Length: 266
Length: 285
Ligand SMILES: [Ca+2]
Ligand SMILES: [Ca+2]
Image: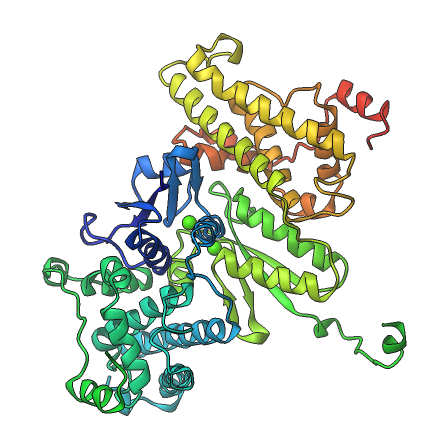
């Protein structure tokens, strides 16, 4: 007597059995998990290879995320449609999953925008150590750090476990995957981690790594790395290809100590 | 506001108003031609509404989604994508693109966005049944040199066609009761930006591939299609017939020979004769 929603997510380009690193797939999967956890929806998630013939013919060129509600004969291929259906369901069963917060919206966009500029600038430059970067590349790195600081500041003013309060919202479903992508790509491709002095931001990342919605929907490190390399036309050798999948959900020991001192975790 | 209007010296530079660039999926036959992506046409129509009244500057550019530069520049995002360079902003997600256009429409008192669950259901139900019929008939005709006529189809294929006609009929009925130029009233809204391209796709694909026209007795609907073919927002953003056909062929994996690949592009915006008369004799145009 509760709706079944099937979510199609883009598969890893390395192994089509593994979930890929599309951020919009993780956003909706997180939302759906939040409804699933509390018995408001039935949810199946399926991986798909977007280059496949059956995929193209079945969705006429739509890309994941795609959500299906067969009991209603409804296919939601557009992100507006998927969000609207999940919002309707959240609202129906009084689940506080959606809120409007222009501050979060701006912080999220601006962080990832600067991340993308830095990723491209540094990869092209390296075709190095961040400390040694010349001004014209280093400025992109600094701007990423500035946005990370801004979110640290926001979390520090709010004193909240999640971005808007003590419960998860659509904005965590967007920011947490972006932060984790920033970490994984930072450490592997760019030469940096999130600055250790941003204790609130790190506490929020710990919160992500303790949130079942995030954990269950999180791609392996190798699949995050391949996602960006593939779109950037960066070669991935077979050693890399064959790496057994891992999920790096660790916090630096000194950061964990700082989190305890300031009381930023349970 | 007039009192206030007398107290504002708002500048007269075309470069005052926001510049929004829309990247649209190109034709897979000739990448210089606009493709048939329905979300691209929806937002282009909305941008044109704002463009034509001087609310925004708008440029449109076609892209081969398979190009290395496009993949690298937008990290896998697909058209439609909207750029507002002067704000350093890139809207890659349809929620973001709509959000920005919605904001601007509101800010300048433009009645472009409304909420209507009648309209939203009718649009979805029409295109859903069209897609079912497209897929069912294409598969039925596999291994035949001459395609089947719709009138000869067995019940489990023909039902999708009948459901298409039912939904077209439902929309005709809604328009007849509303007596409006556009779907919701006198002004183009986002729902027109969704239905008019869908209707035109259905008309072109019906005549060219599936063996049917939008029924000629649906006079109010045909009047609304005529409205489309007289709305600059629609006309300017409308792909050529060959690119609409190719769009569905390339995903339905159907064969495009050298000839229709070399077919010179045309845009068929023609109402049937008796239908145009019916429209005139009811004053629907
Ligand atoms: Ca989608
Ligand atoms: Ca898009």
